[PDB]
Image (cartoon, rainbow over all chains, first blue to last red):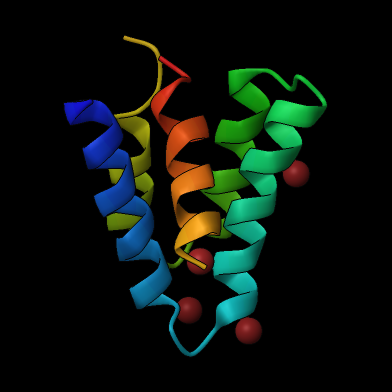
Length: 69
Length: 16
Ligand SMILES: [Br-]
Ligand SMILES: [Br-]
Ligand SMILES: [Br-]
Ligand SMILES: [Br-]
């Protein structure tokens, strides 16, 4: 609920940071869709998001707040 | 749109 709203705010931050690179935003969306559809483990999603946001270290740190513990 | 955004939020918010 609060966590859902925090997730909405975070994904919006990604969308606006990559407003001129929609393919990167789209890739982030597909990482999550693939995670769910292929039942990938957390560590594989962590690897993919780390690579995607290599030049966006603040977005990477924000992502980690959604991970277990 | 906001659909894709809310979908990603739902998946993200359920990993922990
Ligand atoms: Br692009
Ligand atoms: Br992927
Ligand atoms: Br960039
Ligand atoms: Br969207």
